[PDB]
Length: 209
Length: 203
Image (cartoon, chains in turn green, purple):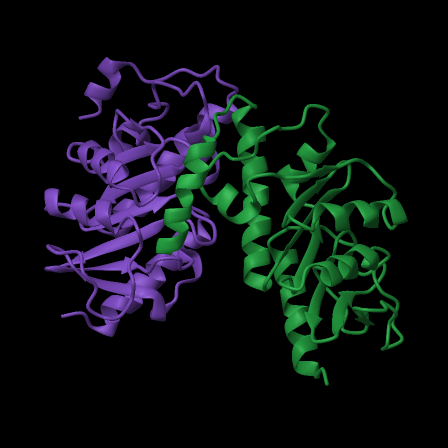
């Protein structure tokens, strides 16, 4: 069913995330649901300059590759999220600049709501997962749990994961996740946040949009 | 009398603001006075990659679109500013790197005049508006009030706004606003400013 048309668009999106510097070289991975199957970046591949030859196809329900190309060593949480979240179509694990700095900090933010776009796009709460070996079962299980009700998670000493309806939403979510972290580091940690009431107020603004 | 030439210039100019990273994705908004009407970026549109289909033509006096494109929320302060400032033709709400860091700071700097370029282009005095919901009447009130006699404004916990007679003046004004903030942060807070006398001398 899936044509080279979808695989070409997947490729350009992977490059687009690489041009935005959401990940460097061989860290991070991407997936995209088309019907009963998903496109996932191949293990050990560079998402910025991605493949074509190293694009894996798996069945979402029994996540074994059908195209005979080995998937991301982290495909378990990619596909897990997709089984879990019927509304989600793209998952991006990346490794941003300031957001990775923060993921490695001993004193992490309790509150990332520094501008309106953060609670609106990234989520009003950002679950933080402790360090697990990349590709470890324990990691997949935590991400899947974290992403049942959240679109954005911080992996400590690793990077971050984001998901959404399409490539643009995922791009938007990734960039603002990065921007929140940039504000926090660059302000020197002495910032103020939106009030709970004020984040609820935004519903009216989101409606109008 | 909006030709496509007007709209194409608006699109190109939106794009150059995006290339400078004055805003990211769907944050910020841009407006341009052309006679009795104004071009405004459409609500929800991404201004760095705008978007012929998402440009609003609005009557300045009334605020209502004529081309089927829903204008930016916050069209209320843009049109507010154009009505009170006949000299102003472009208004940009943006959200750049170091200036937004300053936006969210609990203890803001009180003096931004760190090079000659700041008092010249940005203004010797930058009004700081508290946080109000984007698009809200309270925000419109503050922004319009602050921009009667200033061209540059800091929106707490949000971003910044700039005024100008044209696109070049706005681009420069925004770039130096950001530069002033970049200096403050990179210096680590321990910076000196031009004296009041020295700013008065800049004439």
